[PDB]
Image (cartoon, rainbow, N blue to C red; front, side, top):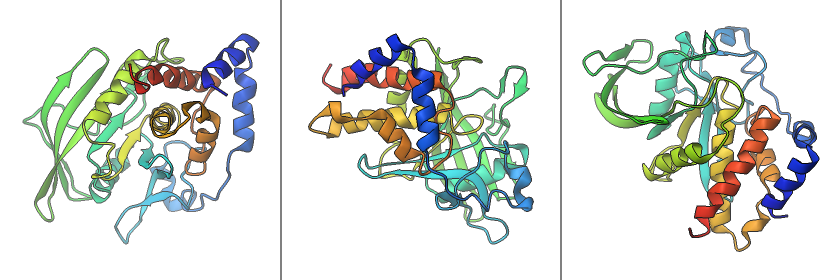
Length: 284
């Protein structure tokens, strides 16, 4: 069923809550035993959001290999993403350790450091060229190279140095700054414009490791980003673009991380973004 028609159908009948609850009922449940170990309580921002053991990212240290992050592997679309929580004060060094070990080219950030008067993630990158950051627990140096501030997003060039080997790499930070404190955006135009800028950079391409994407919990805004990307890529690839079923793709992605898409408003917005973004994918 053409999603666009399915869309008007749900909208006229006002069934978005009932659709979303079907998804929550059919979604996978797998064990997350490593996340719940007592030695990791201060590595988890929220008690009810954990990586499954089968898909979690492991740090390459013998000490404690745990970080609240998951590998979403999309086999038909040939895309992979790492979804993670906003870094905590005790995990900023683990975050950049992961970015290095997994060979990512880009980091995607969908939240502000402060929202609704409270801190949603640590200030984990440097704000001035001449004031670099050193993560002594994981032996890494991070320097701001350049900054391009636009109306709806900011792009930053960062240098990450492994102080153990003195290798350096360029990391691109893509920061969407205008998601509202409550609800979802009214039009998906600026979110789609942002997604295409990430694509154009090479950060989503198979010559690099998976992009790292995060919001506060790493499941809501972050889920919207990867669901919309994967769905548009499948409409490109398939003989019949109408065969792309957004609810089935979301359930496949939830085999890899719990809770992706947090509200019925986020579900609706994901439909809207795919429908509108298809009006370039099909040749316009």
